[PDB]
Image (cartoon, coloured by chain):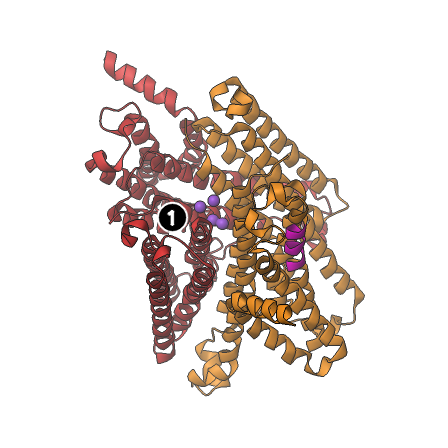
Chain colours: A orange, B red
Amino acid sequence: IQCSQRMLSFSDALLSIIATVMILPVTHTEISPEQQFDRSVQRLLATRIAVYLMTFLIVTVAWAAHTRLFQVVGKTDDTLALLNLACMMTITFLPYTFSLMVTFPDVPLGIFLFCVCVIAIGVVQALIVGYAFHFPHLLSPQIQREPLSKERVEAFSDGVYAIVATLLILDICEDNVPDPKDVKERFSGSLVAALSATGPRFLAYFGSFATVGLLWFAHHSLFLHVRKATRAMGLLNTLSLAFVGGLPLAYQQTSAFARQPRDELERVRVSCTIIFLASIFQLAMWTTALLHQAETLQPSVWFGGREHVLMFAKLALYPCASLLAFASTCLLSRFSVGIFHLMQIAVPCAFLLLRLLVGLALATLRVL
Amino acid sequence: IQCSQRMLSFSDALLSIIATVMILPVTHTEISPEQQFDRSVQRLLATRIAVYLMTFLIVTVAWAAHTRLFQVVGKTDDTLALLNLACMMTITFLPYTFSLMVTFPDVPLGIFLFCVCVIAIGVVQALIVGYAFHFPHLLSPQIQREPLSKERVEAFSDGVYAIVATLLILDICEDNVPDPKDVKERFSGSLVAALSATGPRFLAYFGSFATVGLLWFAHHSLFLHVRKATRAMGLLNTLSLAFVGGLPLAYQQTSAFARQPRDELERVRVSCTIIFLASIFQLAMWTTALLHQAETLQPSVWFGGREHVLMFAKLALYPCASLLAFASTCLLSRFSVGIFHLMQIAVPCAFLLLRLLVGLALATLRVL
Ligand SMILES: [K+]
Ligand SMILES: [K+]
Ligand SMILES: [K+]
Ligand SMILES: [K+]
Ligand SMILES: [K+]
């Protein structure tokens, strides 16, 4: 009998990428200036965002069902591996059916194909269960004779984060790659001078990537001290990942969404809201785990623990900064863009010096 | 001190996706019929293919250096995690510099940025080494006082395979999603009738996905019996993955490459060549491991072992079928397309029945 760890890792990667794909249409929404005040186009954009959210949630539900199934199964086999590949294929077919239904919501074809795909997933998983139970040695020892699998959650989250960070660089690679017919005209053939138009732009990439990379760093930190992953924690993680997938929306440059008519205040508000939603659910995961620390958290991060305050600050850094920037957009709009840039530059430094800042604050409050 | 396994998994995912991204420009090659006989466009397409190969190899070299580094380090830390994030950011910046150099190969800007990025990677890794050695408890026990890390190779391969399988479905989602203004004209508003143009197309997806999914299944099988991963095996795996990344080229539909002028024989030959190159290097990995079976392979797959013939057949199935199809394109061109479709339908069945076919063949040869 074979060890199923790599097969489950492959499934996690596939499903995470599949869930995150549907943000691409959102980033490719073109709004002409003539349609800036057209409510129909704005409604279409909102509908496409809702479609992305629904598809992410559906793929996550399928992934959770798969996780249940292969917690029940445990071991794998050639036949089981091929059946898992068939299940992954059927699941990956879901975005196509959902897109077809979106294009023609009033025709039965989309609903019919979606139902057929769901039934196919069900039948494939039932076949997997039947094969596993027909050979008892392929079952988990407890079954051979609820909690979530932490590694599956971590792999799914890593896939989502990596895909977002990749979409950023794909956007950059197209933003600032001029052609000879463009450089010879805009800059009289001096490519170096094109830095004046491209220098800052790719520099902005460094700011965006960090925002994702540090968010993962928070997640990576939290689950280093997580013992038991509860279903509520899984749901909160799913919401956090769903809102993480929208970071390219607030950070991409070539994206049609980025080229829509807008103002600085609106863009800053949207980016701050997306970051706040992404991070507040990680903070909610941590708070939820704190209620049952005895069974969900390592002793170091329990109340009064050595790592407690550090973890709390690490997870609350982004929500507080995002909320402060959003408030500044309303109270100090004239300098809100500068404050947002300052936040982008400072939050990584705060993460780097976090262990010193926390101790300094603790000592200052103790003496005072 | 923290466990570095998840950080390395995240790095593997990032680097694998980054390596595979550069196939997207290749799939977006638009060749008008007026330029079918224009040698310049064909040369440009070949140059972009070579650029994709070079970028994949460079990203793989960076990933291998990172693997060496964090085999030396072993344990991780908050500062080490942030430094690893910085290193990943610098590495992800490589595609942008390579693309800029490609656009203007005769200007120093591209080479200058590429050199700056490489030096940045070097300095970041040197800082990681210095920090790790300044705190001896963050070093591996042997160092605290060559072989490859199998899990890193497996994670990188899984990332590449998942990205290819995802690119397939992204192509499909755009191939066969008509709009009302298109359905009302081409099919008089009968969306169901559009199956006549869309039915087979997404059906073809099922054929393409399997081809990737089974290739992974072969890889997944081989490394289940691999003890020690040698550097030569790593190089062969890198070549196999590089040629796997070109599967969307031979299987995508909307891709401008797919819409280029062509003939059935040429497309079949290209697809067969790509599949053959992808699988022959897995077979080469297996053969290379066989030379040092005592140190690289589990006893079950040694010469004369129970699983030996099964593994050999599993890894040689695709190369033989691809070579036979390619030969048919020259000897039986009139039926080569049908033979290719038959191969696409049959190879999964051969994989499913492999354990029976191998035994049947062995018995038949023994009695005869
Ligand atoms: K994993
Ligand atoms: K992944
Ligand atoms: K892994
Ligand atoms: K992956
Ligand atoms: K992509």
- In the picture, the quarter occupied by the C terminus of chain B is top left
Over which residues does the magenta segment extend?
A279-287
Q: Does residue B287 appear in the picture of this structure?
A: yes
Q: Which residue is depicted at the point 52% across and 51% down?
A: A158
Q: Which residue has dot 1 on it?
A: B152
| Residue at the bottom extreme, as displayed | A188
| Image vertical order of residue A189 relative to residue B70, above or below | below
Which sits in the foreground, B268 or B185?
Answer: B268
Helix, strand or loop at mark 1:
helix
**Tally of numbered discs:** 1
Which sits in the foreground, A54 or A347?
Answer: A347
Q: Which residue is depicted at the point 67% across and 49% down?
A: B186
Near mark 1 (Cα within 10 A), the count class, few <14, some 14-19 or many ≥20, is some
Residue A73 in the image, given as x and y percentages of width and height: 53, 28
| Residue at the front extreme, as displayed | A367
Q: Along the horizontal axis of the image, is A157 left or right of B353?
A: right
Residue B331 in the image, given as x and y percentages of width and height: 30, 37
**Residue type at mark 1?**
Arg
Q: Which residue is depicted at the point 36% across and 47% down?
A: B153
Q: Which residue is depicted at the point 53% across and 58% down?
A: A217
Q: Is residue B310 magenta?
A: no
